Amino acid sequence: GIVQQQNNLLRAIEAQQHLLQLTVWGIKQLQARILSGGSGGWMEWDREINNYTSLIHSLIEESQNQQEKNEQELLGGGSGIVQQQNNLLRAIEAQQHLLQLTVWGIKQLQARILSGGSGGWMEWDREINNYTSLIHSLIEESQNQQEKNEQELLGGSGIVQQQNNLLRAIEAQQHLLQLTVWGIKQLQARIL
Amino acid sequence: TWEEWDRAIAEYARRIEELIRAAQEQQRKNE
Image 1 (cartoon, rainbow over the protein chains, first blue to last red):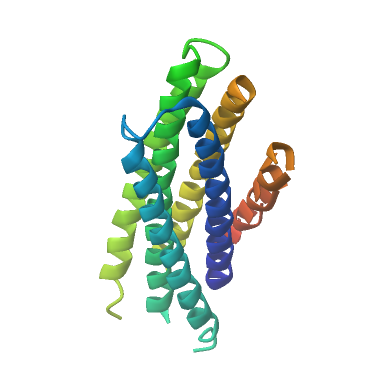
Image 2 (cartoon, rainbow over the protein chains, first blue to last red):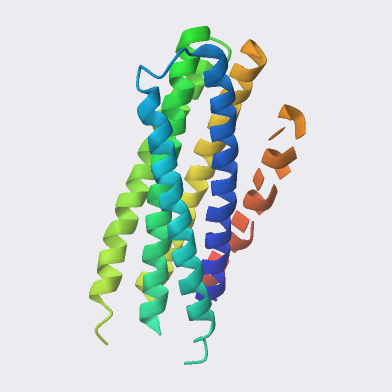
């Protein structure tokens, strides 16, 4: 069932990307109300959002292609499955960069208009720190497992373990994403 | 817009949590 599972992980990544684009929209609404110009790092933010967004689209497109290729070869192919794992990992890392950019943006806006000491903000800040550490450690573990599986291409269990790694990284990203949505709603309700 | 944003989000956030249902109950199987 690895190929099918890879499809579900790819679909989760795509839906997380849409969700991320929505949060980026919300942040831009808020930035237009709170900030003046483009200093404090905002000019760069805008460009980097766009850079990682086009990178992620491109990784999703590559992953789709590999996914179709793997599905056409099910009856024959460890290397296609290992390759797809690399694609999913790269997409997850690019999404993590985007996520860190939205976290930075929410933190800059929050500091202008609200105390960081109340209304759920202290807990928000710890949870962001915790899930950021967790996601980084899962990405590093996925990178190590990916190198091991690639080392074993020269002709099972490493593959299953990497499926678990990817899934757990996607889960932790979803939690980070639900924290960013909460942050945005608190700011929206305050200042719009 | 913010209420029909809030539609879009909870109804992707539906899709994802219930993909992550599926993926985890494949990963049951894998072990």
